[PDB]
Image 1 (cartoon, rainbow, N blue to C red):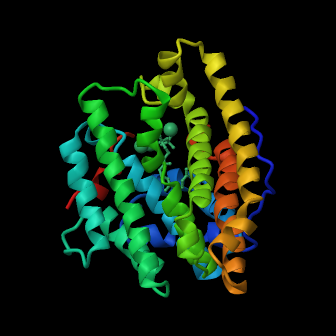
Image 2 (cartoon, rainbow, N blue to C red; image 1 turned 90 degrees about the horizontal axis):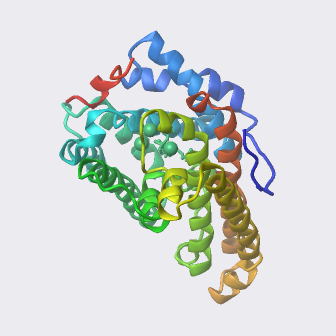
Length: 324
Ligand SMILES: CC(C)=CCC/C(C)=C/CC/C(C)=C(\F)COP(=O)(O)OP(=O)(O)O
Ligand SMILES: [Mg+2]
Ligand SMILES: [Mg+2]
Ligand SMILES: [Mg+2]
């Protein structure tokens, strides 16, 4: 394994054991897991474990919603490992059918992976402000559009020539922002909307995004070499800077450290940011909950899970999830 500077406390929901025990019931009822071998491959992903560390403040049905999001997100992502992920028109055809759930009811003929997302989104929005739902829906659309962009890069044989071009694409496909959004829903709070848009909070969220994708590109480095993948930060640094493999990995460790140090600086600015936006007492507490239960958790929880998950330790078996 490889070590990273993550000076944040590890946390896990106290209801994790029940959530992990019951995690299969929902994707089974939605037709997303259709065999016992698929169920065991799901269990080996550790997706309830991941959700319990993203959402340690959540228990019960709130934590279950977090588990189902992790379950759905990785099932969805596995539909693009084969030829579909090499074809933007076929990628967009699936993402369009899923994203349609944001706009209204799905037709009964929608593929199972789309009905599963619609069930998550319905539970995500109920009880939040309408403006929160609209903003979170926009985050989902950025995520789905990102899959189309990635399929374009593969189809036209245009690999990313620089770290900046990769991040501009990978910051959306990494799915961190929809994960952070659910921490708010799972915690039954909303960070003040004018502070979510602030330059300081945007920089904190960008660090959370960047750290997650750097962690993921290292944890999945072996798999993606064995498939000749070129849009991986390790590979892209070797092309952009002409460096070896051991240098690019050390560069990514230092970047994680530098961004975590900057993240701490930005946290110390939040009291003055609240003053600038004239937050009252309640809004200040909501901002503090966002900092500790949403942004900090998505950084730290990802670090613990990328080391233990079975995804980083039968192709086409999930194809029927994307068939109308
Ligand atoms: C845990 C994180 C980062 C986010 C929370 C769950 C969500 C919404 C994940 C989005 C999908 C994702 C990051 C991958 F599939 C990993 O990237 P990639 O497909 O390149 O590598 P693999 O994980 O498939 O090997
Ligand atoms: Mg994948
Ligand atoms: Mg993928
Ligand atoms: Mg990866």
